[PDB]
Image (cartoon, rainbow, N blue to C red; front, side):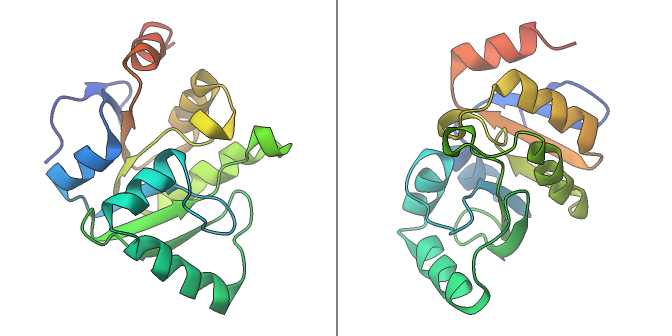
Length: 165
C-alpha cells in the first residue's frame, strides 16, 4: 500500500514524491490528474501522467471529449488509469493563470469524495497558479475520503508541512 507519507489529518496524508513514480509503485485504485476542461494533457502533472501512459491517456481523453464535450471547471470524469492506476479521476481545478474563480477549488476537491482512497496532486497548484498552501487547506477542509497527496517539489513539501495548521 502507500508508504512514507506524513499524516496531516484523520484522512489526509502527504509525501514529497513524483506522482508518476508513486502511481507506478503503488498502482492505486485511483490516481487524480490535474486536468483542464479539454483534457489536453500538455504540461504539469497532466503532461507527466500522460507521457507515462505513452500518450494512451490523451488518445482516450480525445475520444471522451469528442463524445461528451469539455468538462466544467470544478468538475471531473473517471477514465482508465492505464499503466498507472485502475482509474484516473481527471479533476479540473480553477486555473488562476486563465483568470478562473479560486472559489471553484472546493468544488474540484468535492469530486474526491466519490472515491474511498486516492493518490492525488494538490489541485490548482503548479502551473495552475494557485497558492499550494491554500490548496492543501481546501483539501483537508473538503475531502473526507483517504487522500494521499504527492508533492513533487521538496522545498514546497517542506513549506506545506512546516506551515500546516
